[PDB]
Amino acid sequence: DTKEQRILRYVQQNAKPGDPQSVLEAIDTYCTQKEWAMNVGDAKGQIMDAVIREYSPSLVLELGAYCGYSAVRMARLLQPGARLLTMEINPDCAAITQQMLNFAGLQDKVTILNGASQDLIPQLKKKYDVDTLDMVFLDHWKDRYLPDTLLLEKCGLLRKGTVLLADNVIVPGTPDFLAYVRGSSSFECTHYSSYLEYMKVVDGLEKAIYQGP
Ligand SMILES: O=C(NC/C=C/[C@H]1OC[C@H](O)[C@@H]1O)c1cc([N+](=O)[O-])cc(O)c1O
Ligand SMILES: [Cl-]
Ligand SMILES: [Mg+2]
Protein backbone atom coordinates (compact mmCIF):
# COMPACT_ATOMS: atom_id res chain seq x y z
CA ASP A 1 0.00 0.00 0.00
CA THR A 2 1.42 3.41 -1.14
CA LYS A 3 0.62 7.06 -0.40
CA GLU A 4 -0.70 7.48 -3.95
CA GLN A 5 -3.04 4.46 -3.71
CA ARG A 6 -4.37 5.84 -0.42
CA ILE A 7 -5.17 9.15 -2.18
CA LEU A 8 -6.98 7.33 -5.02
CA ARG A 9 -8.97 5.25 -2.53
CA TYR A 10 -9.92 8.37 -0.56
CA VAL A 11 -11.16 9.97 -3.80
CA GLN A 12 -13.18 6.83 -4.66
CA GLN A 13 -14.70 6.84 -1.18
CA ASN A 14 -15.49 10.58 -0.86
CA ALA A 15 -15.76 12.41 -4.19
CA LYS A 16 -18.81 12.44 -6.49
CA PRO A 17 -18.21 10.37 -9.61
CA GLY A 18 -18.19 12.40 -12.88
CA ASP A 19 -17.59 15.66 -10.90
CA PRO A 20 -13.98 16.98 -11.46
CA GLN A 21 -14.32 19.73 -8.86
CA SER A 22 -15.27 17.18 -6.22
CA VAL A 23 -12.21 15.02 -7.07
CA LEU A 24 -9.88 18.07 -6.73
CA GLU A 25 -11.48 18.98 -3.43
CA ALA A 26 -11.10 15.45 -2.00
CA ILE A 27 -7.41 15.28 -3.04
CA ASP A 28 -6.78 18.70 -1.49
CA THR A 29 -8.56 17.68 1.74
CA TYR A 30 -6.60 14.44 2.09
CA CYS A 31 -3.24 16.08 1.42
CA THR A 32 -4.06 18.98 3.77
CA GLN A 33 -5.29 16.83 6.71
CA LYS A 34 -3.64 13.39 6.43
CA GLU A 35 -0.58 13.24 4.13
CA TRP A 36 1.33 15.93 2.22
CA ALA A 37 1.84 15.17 -1.46
CA MET A 38 3.30 16.97 -4.47
CA ASN A 39 0.03 17.90 -6.24
CA VAL A 40 0.02 21.46 -7.61
CA GLY A 41 -2.58 22.32 -5.03
CA ASP A 42 -5.45 24.74 -4.98
CA ALA A 43 -3.52 28.02 -4.70
CA LYS A 44 -1.31 27.41 -7.74
CA GLY A 45 -4.21 25.56 -9.26
CA GLN A 46 -6.36 28.74 -9.36
CA ILE A 47 -3.57 30.45 -11.23
CA MET A 48 -3.38 27.51 -13.68
CA ASP A 49 -7.19 27.71 -14.17
CA ALA A 50 -6.89 31.44 -15.02
CA VAL A 51 -4.13 30.83 -17.57
CA ILE A 52 -5.98 27.93 -19.25
CA ARG A 53 -9.19 30.03 -19.49
CA GLU A 54 -7.25 32.91 -21.00
CA TYR A 55 -5.62 30.88 -23.79
CA SER A 56 -8.34 28.26 -24.44
CA PRO A 57 -5.79 25.69 -25.68
CA SER A 58 -6.90 22.97 -28.11
CA LEU A 59 -3.80 20.69 -27.43
CA VAL A 60 -2.01 20.64 -24.05
CA LEU A 61 1.05 18.56 -23.04
CA GLU A 62 1.64 17.86 -19.38
CA LEU A 63 5.08 16.67 -18.24
CA GLY A 64 4.61 14.69 -15.04
CA ALA A 65 1.09 13.46 -14.20
CA TYR A 66 1.77 12.09 -10.71
CA CYS A 67 -1.73 11.24 -9.32
CA GLY A 68 -3.52 13.20 -12.04
CA TYR A 69 -4.50 16.25 -9.96
CA SER A 70 -3.31 18.77 -12.55
CA ALA A 71 -4.58 16.53 -15.37
CA VAL A 72 -8.07 16.73 -13.81
CA ARG A 73 -7.64 20.44 -13.15
CA MET A 74 -6.72 21.21 -16.73
CA ALA A 75 -8.97 18.76 -18.57
CA ARG A 76 -12.14 20.02 -16.76
CA LEU A 77 -11.58 23.45 -18.45
CA LEU A 78 -10.87 22.18 -21.91
CA GLN A 79 -13.42 23.00 -24.63
CA PRO A 80 -15.15 20.15 -26.43
CA GLY A 81 -12.74 18.45 -28.92
CA ALA A 82 -9.61 19.72 -27.10
CA ARG A 83 -7.04 17.17 -25.86
CA LEU A 84 -4.59 16.78 -22.95
CA LEU A 85 -1.58 14.46 -23.32
CA THR A 86 0.15 13.71 -20.02
CA MET A 87 3.56 11.93 -19.60
CA GLU A 88 4.30 9.92 -16.48
CA ILE A 89 7.55 8.04 -15.93
CA ASN A 90 6.22 5.83 -13.08
CA PRO A 91 3.77 3.09 -14.20
CA ASP A 92 2.11 2.94 -10.74
CA CYS A 93 1.41 6.71 -10.89
CA ALA A 94 0.33 6.41 -14.54
CA ALA A 95 -2.23 3.76 -13.49
CA ILE A 96 -3.46 5.92 -10.59
CA THR A 97 -3.74 8.92 -12.92
CA GLN A 98 -5.89 6.88 -15.33
CA GLN A 99 -8.19 5.85 -12.48
CA MET A 100 -8.44 9.46 -11.23
CA LEU A 101 -9.45 10.69 -14.67
CA ASN A 102 -11.93 7.80 -15.10
CA PHE A 103 -13.61 8.70 -11.82
CA ALA A 104 -13.79 12.36 -12.78
CA GLY A 105 -15.40 11.48 -16.13
CA LEU A 106 -12.52 13.06 -18.06
CA GLN A 107 -11.02 9.96 -19.67
CA ASP A 108 -12.22 10.95 -23.13
CA LYS A 109 -10.16 14.14 -23.20
CA VAL A 110 -6.86 12.77 -21.73
CA THR A 111 -4.22 10.41 -23.13
CA ILE A 112 -1.60 9.00 -20.68
CA LEU A 113 1.85 8.33 -22.06
CA ASN A 114 4.00 5.99 -19.88
CA GLY A 115 7.67 6.74 -20.24
CA ALA A 116 10.42 9.27 -19.74
CA SER A 117 9.72 12.65 -21.32
CA GLN A 118 12.98 12.54 -23.34
CA ASP A 119 11.94 9.26 -24.93
CA LEU A 120 8.23 10.19 -25.51
CA ILE A 121 8.62 13.78 -26.88
CA PRO A 122 10.19 12.65 -30.18
CA GLN A 123 7.31 10.20 -30.71
CA LEU A 124 4.45 12.70 -30.21
CA LYS A 125 3.88 13.90 -33.77
CA LYS A 126 3.87 10.48 -35.44
CA LYS A 127 2.29 8.33 -32.72
CA TYR A 128 -0.16 10.85 -31.27
CA ASP A 129 -1.18 12.91 -34.34
CA VAL A 130 0.29 16.16 -33.03
CA ASP A 131 1.45 19.08 -35.14
CA THR A 132 2.27 21.81 -32.58
CA LEU A 133 1.30 22.26 -28.95
CA ASP A 134 -0.79 25.19 -27.73
CA MET A 135 0.31 24.84 -24.12
CA VAL A 136 2.81 22.82 -22.03
CA PHE A 137 2.66 22.28 -18.33
CA LEU A 138 6.04 21.40 -16.74
CA ASP A 139 5.82 19.60 -13.38
CA HIS A 140 8.19 16.61 -13.68
CA TRP A 141 11.78 16.21 -12.52
CA LYS A 142 13.07 19.73 -12.01
CA ASP A 143 16.37 19.00 -13.75
CA ARG A 144 14.37 18.00 -16.86
CA TYR A 145 12.61 21.27 -17.45
CA LEU A 146 15.37 22.85 -19.53
CA PRO A 147 16.50 19.81 -21.52
CA ASP A 148 12.85 18.85 -22.30
CA THR A 149 12.13 22.43 -23.44
CA LEU A 150 15.13 22.27 -25.78
CA LEU A 151 13.84 18.89 -27.05
CA LEU A 152 10.31 20.29 -27.66
CA GLU A 153 11.86 23.01 -29.67
CA LYS A 154 14.22 20.56 -31.58
CA CYS A 155 11.28 18.33 -32.47
CA GLY A 156 9.22 21.22 -33.90
CA LEU A 157 6.52 21.03 -31.23
CA LEU A 158 6.46 24.75 -30.32
CA ARG A 159 4.87 27.46 -32.46
CA LYS A 160 4.79 31.22 -31.99
CA GLY A 161 2.45 31.76 -29.00
CA THR A 162 2.84 28.28 -27.42
CA VAL A 163 2.48 28.84 -23.70
CA LEU A 164 4.87 27.06 -21.33
CA LEU A 165 3.73 27.08 -17.76
CA ALA A 166 6.19 25.72 -15.18
CA ASP A 167 5.51 24.69 -11.57
CA ASN A 168 8.01 24.91 -8.70
CA VAL A 169 10.30 27.47 -10.24
CA ILE A 170 11.19 28.71 -6.70
CA VAL A 171 10.67 25.57 -4.56
CA PRO A 172 12.28 23.11 -5.07
CA GLY A 173 13.38 25.39 -7.92
CA THR A 174 14.43 25.11 -11.56
CA PRO A 175 17.21 27.62 -11.73
CA ASP A 176 18.70 26.58 -15.13
CA PHE A 177 15.28 26.65 -16.81
CA LEU A 178 14.36 29.97 -15.29
CA ALA A 179 17.68 31.62 -16.27
CA TYR A 180 17.31 30.26 -19.77
CA VAL A 181 13.74 31.33 -20.59
CA ARG A 182 14.23 34.75 -18.90
CA GLY A 183 17.46 35.32 -20.85
CA SER A 184 16.19 34.16 -24.25
CA SER A 185 14.65 36.35 -26.93
CA SER A 186 12.63 33.27 -27.93
CA PHE A 187 10.54 33.49 -24.73
CA GLU A 188 8.41 36.23 -23.13
CA CYS A 189 8.16 35.42 -19.46
CA THR A 190 5.79 36.27 -16.62
CA HIS A 191 6.15 35.14 -13.00
CA TYR A 192 3.05 34.33 -10.87
CA SER A 193 3.88 34.37 -7.19
CA SER A 194 2.08 31.82 -5.06
CA TYR A 195 2.66 29.13 -2.40
CA LEU A 196 3.96 25.60 -2.34
CA GLU A 197 0.99 23.20 -2.26
CA TYR A 198 -0.58 22.65 1.18
CA MET A 199 2.01 25.02 2.83
CA LYS A 200 3.07 28.68 3.65
CA VAL A 201 6.37 28.47 1.72
CA VAL A 202 6.62 30.92 -1.24
CA ASP A 203 6.67 29.25 -4.70
CA GLY A 204 5.52 30.33 -8.17
CA LEU A 205 4.61 29.42 -11.69
CA GLU A 206 6.49 30.83 -14.66
CA LYS A 207 4.73 31.45 -17.90
CA ALA A 208 7.04 31.49 -20.88
CA ILE A 209 5.47 32.21 -24.29
CA TYR A 210 7.52 31.00 -27.18
CA GLN A 211 8.18 33.74 -29.74
CA GLY A 212 9.71 31.72 -32.59
CA PRO A 213 13.33 30.70 -33.45
O1 LIG B 1 9.65 16.58 -7.46
C1 LIG B 1 8.56 17.10 -7.76
N1 LIG B 1 7.93 16.74 -8.91
C2 LIG B 1 8.58 15.86 -9.84
C3 LIG B 1 8.18 14.43 -9.66
C4 LIG B 1 8.09 13.59 -10.69
C5 LIG B 1 7.69 12.16 -10.54
O2 LIG B 1 7.84 11.65 -9.19
C6 LIG B 1 6.65 10.93 -8.80
C7 LIG B 1 5.84 10.70 -10.09
O3 LIG B 1 6.36 9.59 -10.79
C8 LIG B 1 6.18 12.01 -10.87
O4 LIG B 1 6.00 12.09 -12.29
C9 LIG B 1 7.94 18.08 -6.83
C10 LIG B 1 8.44 18.23 -5.53
C11 LIG B 1 7.87 19.15 -4.67
N2 LIG B 1 8.49 19.23 -3.34
O5 LIG B 1 8.20 20.11 -2.56
O6 LIG B 1 9.29 18.38 -3.11
C12 LIG B 1 6.75 19.93 -5.06
C13 LIG B 1 6.24 19.74 -6.34
O7 LIG B 1 5.16 20.51 -6.70
C14 LIG B 1 6.82 18.84 -7.24
O8 LIG B 1 6.27 18.77 -8.48
CL1 LIG C 1 -0.49 17.62 -9.85
MG1 LIG D 1 4.97 20.52 -8.70
Image (cartoon, helix red, strand yellow):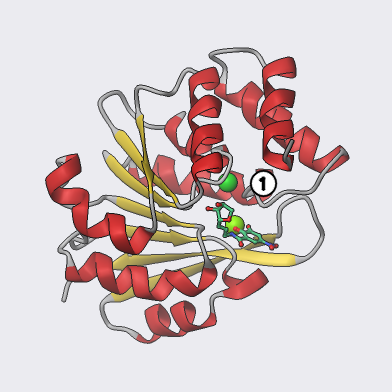
Q: Quadrant of residue 79?
A: top left
User: Label 1 neighbourhood size at 10 Å, few (<14), some (14-19), many (20+)?
Assistant: many
Q: Quadrant of residue 195?
A: bottom right
Image side of residue 185 versus residue 104, left or right: left
Q: Is mark 1 within 8 Å of ligand 1?
A: yes
Q: Residue at x 46, y 52 (%)?
A: 89
Q: Nearer the viewer, residue 64 or 193?
A: 64
Q: Residue at x 64, y 31 (%)?
A: 24
Image side of residue 1 versus residue 181, left or right: right
Image side of residue 186 versus residue 48, left or right: left
Q: Residue furthest right?
A: 33
The percent coordinates of residue 154 (x first, y second) are 18, 71
Ligand 3 sits in which quadrant? bottom right
- Is 25 located above or below residue 142 in the figure? above
Residue 124 seen in the current view: yes
The percent coordinates of residue 1 (x first, y second) are 74, 35
Q: Nearer the viewer, residue 22 or 101?
A: 101
Q: Residue at x 26, y 69 (%)?
A: 151
Q: How many marks?
A: 1
Q: Amino acid at mark 1?
A: Gly
Residue 162 seen in the current view: no
The percent coordinates of residue 50 (x first, y second) are 50, 45
| Residue picked out by circle 1 | 41
Assign the C terminus to one quadrant of the image. bottom left
The percent coordinates of residue 33 (x first, y second) are 87, 39
Q: Tag 1, which secondary structure? A: helix
Q: Residue furthest top?
A: 17
